[PDB]
Image: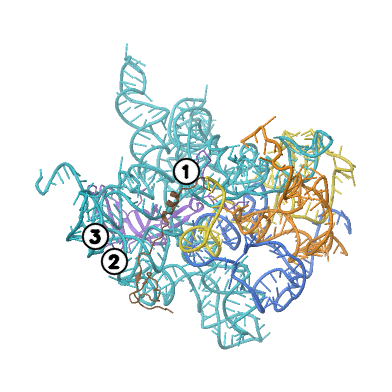
Chain colours: A brown, B purple, C orange, D blue, E yellow, F cyan
Amino acid sequence: AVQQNKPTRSKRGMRRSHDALTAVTSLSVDKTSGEKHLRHHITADGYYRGRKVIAK
Amino acid sequence: MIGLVGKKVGMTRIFTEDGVSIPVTVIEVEANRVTQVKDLANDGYRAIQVTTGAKKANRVTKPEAGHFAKAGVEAGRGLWEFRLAEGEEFTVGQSISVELFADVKKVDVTGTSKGKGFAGTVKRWNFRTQDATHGNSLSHRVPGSIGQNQTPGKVFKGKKMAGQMGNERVTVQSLDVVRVDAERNLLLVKGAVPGATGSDLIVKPAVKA
RNA sequence: AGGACCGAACCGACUAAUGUUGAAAAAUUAGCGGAUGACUUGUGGCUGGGGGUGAAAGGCCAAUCAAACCGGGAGAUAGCU
RNA sequence: CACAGGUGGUCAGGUAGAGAAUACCAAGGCGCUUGAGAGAACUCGGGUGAAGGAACUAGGCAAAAUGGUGCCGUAACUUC
RNA sequence: AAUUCCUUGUCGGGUAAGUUCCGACCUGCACGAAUGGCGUAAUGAUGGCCAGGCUGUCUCCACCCGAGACUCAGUGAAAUU
RNA sequence: GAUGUCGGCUCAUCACAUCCUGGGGCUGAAGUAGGUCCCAAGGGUAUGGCUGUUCGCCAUUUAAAGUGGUACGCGAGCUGGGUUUAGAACGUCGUGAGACAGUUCGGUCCCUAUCUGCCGUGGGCGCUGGAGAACUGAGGGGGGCUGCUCCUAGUACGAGAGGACCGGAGUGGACGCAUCACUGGUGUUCGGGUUGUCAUGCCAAUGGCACUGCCCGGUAGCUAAAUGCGGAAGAGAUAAGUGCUGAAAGCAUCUAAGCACGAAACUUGCCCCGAGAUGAGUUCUCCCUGACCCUUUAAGGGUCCUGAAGGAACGUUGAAGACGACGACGUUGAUAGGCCGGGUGUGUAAGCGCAGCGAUGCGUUGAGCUAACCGGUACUAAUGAACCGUGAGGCUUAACCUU
C-alpha cells in the first residue's frame, strides 16, 4: 500500500522520461489568407482552405 | 502439401438430400500467385512465397513493387509462405487455384481470432465467480489468491491473470471439405473458423490425417 | 372504549450493501419497529464527581467515564525501557 | 469545510387518491462550483434471462415474490 | 432440557441420506417448586426446525443501462520513508 | 515498539510412499475377477443429507473420488459459522466479587501498490548506410484424461456357471480452443400495447415524467445452454521386465565384448510465442553517385546546395483497442456519416371515407415506421503543403576482377 523506502530523485526522473510534451510538427498555411493554422482546422480569421468560412 | 490463402466470406448452411444441415464457413480463395521460390542452396529451406487479391497501385511501396516486378505478377494484399514437402515443384509467377483442394477431404484453417481486448479471469480463463451475496465485499469476479505464503514468496510465471484476449493466431484442425467450387473460387468447410468476416485465412490439408 | 389495529408526519434503529485517508470522528441507500401513549417536542429550571442520574448497560453526566473536566501538590514515584 | 448530518413554529393550490402517502403539475424556486472524451478488466447502483428451482450457505444473507376494494369463505386452539 | 459430560444416548417421525428439529424413554455427570415448578390463548425487527410460493443464492454465468476506473485540460492530497 | 487463527470460498504449486489410466514379475494366476511386489507423476482424481467443523457417518455417483509439502499454501484476495472482549441466562463451583476450555442467545474484518513478483501493453536505443517486406528456429509455453456399446466371439478357457487377451469400429462424460449458420439469452439506440399526469390553444395526433412508468416482441453486436474441432497415430532413446549369442568359471549364465525387444514418463511429432538468440541470423526488393572551407589531420569539424526510398504527423476510421499499439482509407477516393435500394423487426400509421347513439369496427393497407445489417452512391468530411529521414556507407586479413 505504501513504500518501504524513499524513491530516489534518479528514479523520479526515470519515470518522467515519458512525460515530455510533443510540439506540433508544422502548421499549415492558408492558400489565400496566408496565415498559419492547425491542419484541418479553420484559421483564426475564419478561413479554411481559402474559402472564408463564417467569421462573424 | 502446400496450402492457399483466402478470405472469410461468412457462414451459411448446406441442406443435404437426406435432411441434414451442415454448418459451413465460406472461404473465398482467389488464385494464389507465386512471388518467390526458396531453395536450400540460396535460402537453406524449400518453400514458396505467394500473394493473393489486389492492392492499390498508389499504396504499393517501391520496395514492394520491385519484389512483385521481379516475379512478373500483380501486387496482392500480402505475402505468405508455404513449406514444400520434398516433392513439390513450383515456378515464379505460377497461379494456384482452389482446385488444389479437390481431393483433400480435410483441411487446417488458420486465422486471427476476434479481439476481446482486456479480458478478466472469468472470461479469459473460466475462473469460478465467488459468491454474489453472503457477505462478499467487492470480490465478486476478482481472481482470488494468486500464490502461497512466504515459502514461494513470489507469483509463479505463467500464472493465469487478466489481460489481452483474442486477436491472435489460431488454428482449427481437421475440418471436412464440404465443397470446392472452382468456378466461383469458393471453398466450403464444415464448422467455424477463427476470425471475423473479411479476415485472411490460411487453408492447408489436415496434418493429423 | 383501547399502553387496540393498518399507515404518513414525528420518534426510533432489526437486516443488508456502500462508505472505512468516508459526503459523515456512526452516516447514506433499500427494507424495518412504535406511531392517543410507560408517546413525542420547544423554552426555562433543579440534581455535581466517590457525587449525580439510571424501566439497570457500569449506562449517561459537553465527541472524555470501573470515578468528568480545569488548575494546583508536581520535576508524584518508575529496582522498568 | 460553501460538509449528502442536526435544527422549533406558521402557510398548505390542481388531477388521480382514503390521505399531509404516491405520481405528474401551479405559484415559486432550482440543475446541487471541475469539465471534455473513451465505451477495457474490476468495483459500485440497477434491468433482463434458456433449462433447473435453495442443489447456495453457518443460515433462503441478498434477491425474487405477496401487495388494492367489494363479495363469498375461513382450521387447531382459546383467557371467548 | 437455554441444564445431559459420556453423546451424534436409544426408539419413532420427517429426508434418497437429518450431530439440527419434533414425539417418547429415564442411565436427571450436575431439574425441581416465589433467586418459584409445570402449563398457557394472545403477543415478539426473539432462538431452532419443516413446507408451498418465489427466485441469478446456486449449477454457470451472459447481455444490457448508468456512476467510477482509462485518455485530455485545470486544481491538487495522504499514510510511509 | 503486533509474524491475525479453525473451517468455507477463490486460486493454486510441488513431492511420489500411485487412487485411476499405462508397462511388468510372482501367485494357493483355468477364464472373468483378484492378491502382492517392481517401474511409472503425462493427464485425470464426485455431488449431496447432518454438523461451524476438518474429520466422520449416511444417500447416490465415478475409470478413480490418492497420500503428503507449500506460515497445519492462500483474510494488504473474500467470508466470519467456530475460537477469543464488553450483554444475558442455565448447570456447576464459591459466603461473595466472579469462575468453567461446560452449554446457550447476541455481538464493527481498515489499507488509493513504492519495490520484488506475475498478467498484459508501449516508448527508447541497439543490431554498423538507410528503408519496406517475407523468413530461418536457438529457446520458451500450450496440449497429453477417460467411460460405455458393438465386431472379433459366446470363440480361447471352463464339468458347469461364467467368460477373455490381442486387434478393429462406433458413440459419450469432463476439459480446452474457436465460432454465431442453426436453437436461444440479451438487445434502456427498433416497433407496438397500456395506467396516471402535464404540456403542445382546442379536437385529433404527439411529446415529457413516473425503475426503460409498467409491459409485449425484436435488428446488429456480444454470448451458451447453441455447433464445429482437439487429446492421437508415428519416430528416437529408455524404466521395471523379457531375450539372443557368449566367456571369465570346459558346465551354467540377458553381460563382462557384441546384439534385439520394452510404458500415458523422457526427446520428437501437434498448436502458439519467438533473432534484445548483444551468439542481435537469413532471403528478396527499394533509395541516395554534390561544391568548398578550417585545423590539434581524423571513423574530425563547419558552410552552401541537396531532402531520395521511406517514416511520422494530421484527417476519415475499424468485427483493433484502457492509453500507446495494430489494420483500412485520404479525391488517381467507398474510410466514416448521409443518401438510394433491399433486408429485418414491429404488426394494418396518419389523414380521409363508411357502419354504429357510443366505446369501437371496417376500407384505403401487411399500412406506417424501422439502430448497429446487406448491395450501391462522392452529397459532407478525409487540402496543396509542411515535418522527420540524406548525399554511396570504418579498419585488418584472405580468395577472386588480374583462375
Q: Residues within 10 Å of mark 3 (few under 14, many from 20)?
A: few
**Does mark 3 fall on the same chain as mark 2?**
yes
Q: Which mark is residue B156?
A: 1
Question: Residue B58 got which mark?
Answer: 2
The answer to which of B56 and F167 lies nearer the viewer is: B56
* Position in image of residue F203 (x %, y %): 62, 84
**Chain-order first, disc 1 or disc 3:** 3
Mark positioned earlier in the residue sequence (1 or 2): 2
Residue F351 x/y as whole percent: 55, 85
Asked if badges 1 and 2 are on one and the same chain, I answer yes
Left/right placement of residue F342 relative to residue B184 reads right
Q: Amino acid at mark 1?
A: Phe
Q: Chain of mark 2?
A: B
Asked if residue F260 is positioned above or below residue F89 in the image, the reply reads above
Q: Residue at x 47, y 43 (%)?
A: B156
Residue B19 shows up from this direction:
no
Give, as a three-letter code, the residue at label 2: Asn
Residue to which mark 3 is pinned: B66
How far across and how far down the image is residue E76, in percent? 53, 58
Q: Report the front residue among F222 and C17.
A: C17
